Structures are given as structure tokens and as C-alpha cells.
Image (cartoon, coloured by chain):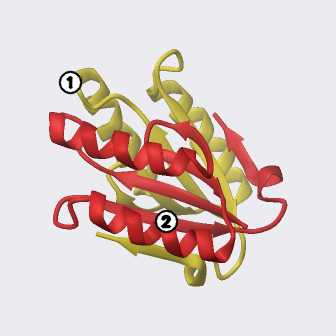
Chain colours: A red, B yellow
Amino acid sequence: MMVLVTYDVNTETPAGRKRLRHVAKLCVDYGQRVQNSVFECSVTPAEFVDIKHRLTQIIDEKTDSIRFYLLGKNWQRRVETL
Amino acid sequence: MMVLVTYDVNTETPAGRKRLRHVAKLCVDYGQRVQNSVFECSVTPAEFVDIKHRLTQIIDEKTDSIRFYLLGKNWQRRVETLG
């Protein structure tokens, strides 16, 4: 299944860029980094669980957020770019 | 149509932050800013055409990008968050 991962982290500090790079390393194991902080991940339900668990320890939960959008099959036919 | 807008701009520059302010100002007329550079927009097909033209005039197409994800009905029940 496809999960779109959008990570909101402030990249104006070294710590924030460090977390973005850690998140990117994790997410790119399961998909494509289509934008600096947006990942298209192809994951089984158990891979998705594992990913969330790992993402929890990396982010600063007070200042960052991650959103996960469960996109349908044929989601590729429903993305446009400007 | 529910359209997720994701804007990649370099906020380390004041020009990039300015563009993001103008992107957000536009997008929040059509939806909700859910993260710094992510917008959940509910638009008609005509509004979507207009919004794209407007965004094209704001972003720097050499350095920035925008992606639009057309989400299905009840997408609200298929978004999970951390942080």
C-alpha cells in the first residue's frame, strides 16, 4: 500500500536538518523522496507500523509533525505537479 | 475535489520564506494549512485551474516545486499524524 509521508521540521537549524536527514534515510528505504520533506512510501501494513514506531523516536514531538496519507491503489494517476 | 498541496521551498532564505507566505495566503483561501508547507484544499475544478495559474506566478519554478494529490472521498478517515 501507498503512504504519503509529509514531515514538518524547521530546517533553519542544524538539529532540524539532522532530523530531516534521519527521517529521509528511514523513508527512502521504502519509497521515493519526491520533495525535500515528502516521501512516497510503498509499505505492507506491518512495515507501516514499524516505520511509525521508528519515526516517533527521531522527531521532536514538541516542534515537528508527520502526516501520513493512505493513498488509494492507482494513486500515481492522481498526482499532478505544477 | 479535495486536493493536498505540498510546497517545497527553501525557508533558509528570506525570499523563500516570502514565497511561502504568499503560497499560504492563497491556499488558505481554499483550505486549511495543516503543516508549514502542506495544505488541505477543497476546490472546484475551475478553482483548481485558477489556483494553479496563481501559484505559477508566485513560486520560483527553477528552485521550488508543488505537488497536488487528489484525495478520494472520506480521505479525512485515512490521515494519521505524529507530533
Image x and y of residue A46, in percent: 61, 76
Q: Quadrant of residue A24?
A: top left
Q: Position of residue B2 (x, y in %)?
A: 63, 66
Separation of residues labelled 1 and 2 (CA atoms): 34 Å
Residue where numbered disc 1 is placed: B14
Q: Which residue is mark 2?
A: A51
The numbered mark 1 sits on a residue in which chain?
A: B
Relative to A78, does residue B53 appear above or below in the rendering?
above
Subunit of mark 2? A
- Taking the spot 20% from the left edge, 24% from the top edge, the residue there is B14
Residue B23, visible in the rendered structure: yes
Q: Residue B54 at what x, y percent from top left?
A: 53, 35
**Front residue of B67 and A1:** A1
Q: Amino acid at mark 2?
A: Ile
Q: Around disc 2, counting alpha carbons within 10 Å, would you say few (fewer than 14), some (14 to 19), or many (20 or more)?
A: some
Q: Residue at x 34, y 37 (%)?
A: B20
Disc 1 versus disc 2: nearer the observer: 2
- Relative image position of residue B31 (x, y in whole percent): 47, 63
Q: Secondary structure at mark 1?
A: helix
**Which residue is drawn at the image coordinates 28% and 65% (left, top)?**
A57
